Image (tube, rainbow, N blue to C red; front, side, top):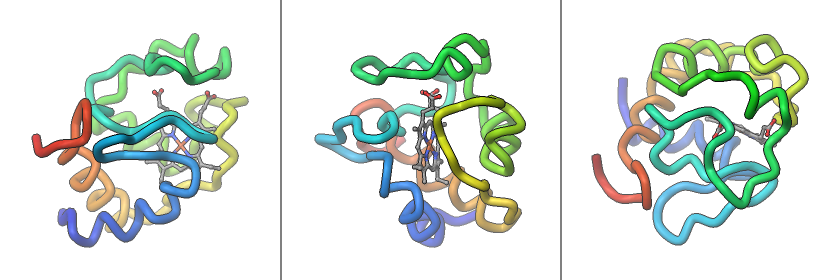
Length: 107
Ligand code: HEC
């Protein structure tokens, strides 16, 4: 779906997470270069065992399921959020993010 739209839905994400350039960790790990990266991999982030010992590897398909309801895919994770149980939204989320990658740029 669409990114311009998806930027809106990340608003409820930015509260704890960063993206783009000069993105530094916060209550949660920066979401730069998310797709492909290994779960609990970004450094300077005190991941939970649950997150980092999962072996997830964040592909669009598992994020799609995660975001829907976190506690169910990484049961016991530190991310206390009742997901994006909203299908239009999730798709645009996965458009905006995918757009940054690694150091916050376009690809
Ligand atoms: C504050 C309450 C948060 C909101 C709102 C969102 N996220 Fe989050 N996220 C938060 C924490 C504390 C953590 C760490 C979990 C742990 O157990 O260590 C996370 C983690 C993620 C991850 C995992 C990343 C990795 O490198 O493994 C992802 C993919 C993620 N968060 C995505 C995400 C998105 C897209 C959100 C908007 C809908 C979102 N989170 C909300 C804190 C918070």
